[PDB]
Length: 210
Length: 188
Length: 210
Ligand SMILES: [Mg+2]
Image 1: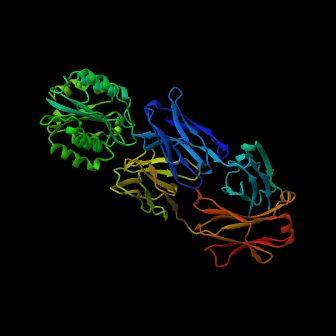
Image 2: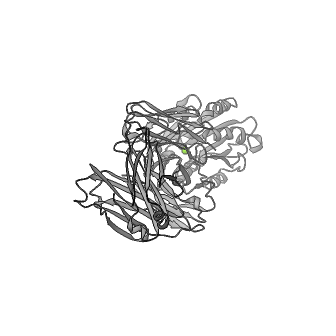
């Protein structure tokens, strides 16, 4: 089936450069005009650049002169070279297939996260949150950048779980997660939150003890 | 004796540009071009319109073949067919650009998609009749093959009556060459 | 240049209701496109060429319009249709999206389950002290939380996070985190979290001492 897969996102400092790539499959790539669309955190969609099957490129004012869209048909890949990055360029970048002259975004990948900041990569501090049914949880405080993975009992305990969106304050994220189980389950049966922060290669299984 | 102006769609959608040029070629080589023969001008359009060369820049049929095969696709995030036709009508077909007083005006439009500015297409076509310009329209159905119906009615409405002896329909950019014969020997 | 304004900015409706979203362009366009985006996911092609449904889009959806006014209509709002819908035009450069319409599903009012959690002793050892309060599965999503240290309201180091509408029960949840230093925290004794919601006249109150 038709598919696109973005790559290259990550933390980069203001004034830095970053190269995104997109692998296409399931269709005759070279015949389609391709684009990149971005979505800053908590905001709308914004088309960024486009390249026709003929090699013609067009750009959004805020990026022309800094970003360069290109394609390599021998590898069915699309690229986005981003220079002079600014904090405002922070967003999830989507590779997208166009229809007609390219203005209808036919296919979207899952996206890649580009974070533009001076903040330093930092590991999260995971703290246990203990008190008919009981509510427990864990505070995942002070990490950067996103993302962070959170599950309970390795994902076997998925019901009654509430993982709240991270809140950014002073260059550090923080998020909480709560899980509710019958009172006759804890502490007789074990409850632990699994948290991983790939950017700092951190893994931790924090058991919730009364 | 008739000045011919070809209005070429060069938007992002057109692909490959090689077959389009092979079409011009196979069509322009069968003509006797000269100041007292048959002149030809080419206009390319996409988001915007640009004159490749005027009706009288070249007086030789060979000089036209070489310049033609030199035309580059300009791309376009839109297919402004109305803007392209209207621009050929009031800019290309003007004495200033080589139009010969008294001679028969002929416009050849080639497109592969509904225009983004189809809301002024009626007005633009009517103004072509008012200036007595014979119109031949060629529609490439590739991208649609999605019904091509509405697309077909639009391109036909561009051709002069009778539709049957002015409007063409091809499967894709490659099939364009299978028209040069009928196309030419119908412009006589 | 063409700007798109969607209305309403957001809406609330019951299942079975006929819902209609509008997209007005600052200049006429001959076609409109729509995409559906759910929390944390890539936008999905929904309607193209004004009224064609993209593959997989259920029959209750339809699109219409001309000139500068286009619409998207859901004949019978289902719980799975909650999302932010974006209109988009390919007629003017740069291509652009509307700011989107966030659609939510109505359901029976439900009181929030509040749980308060004292600082982890694991956190105290590092100088900090965060108190957490979870307000789970309530509706409507309008809610208020006030922190009261030793009877006196306090709200300088409070950070809140709200989840999007639950894909399972259409409810809402939110957590409130009050961060103080180990010293401030030990300076006081009773900590309480107050939740005001249309479900009850008086605030649901939870708290603890030391
Ligand atoms: Mg076109």
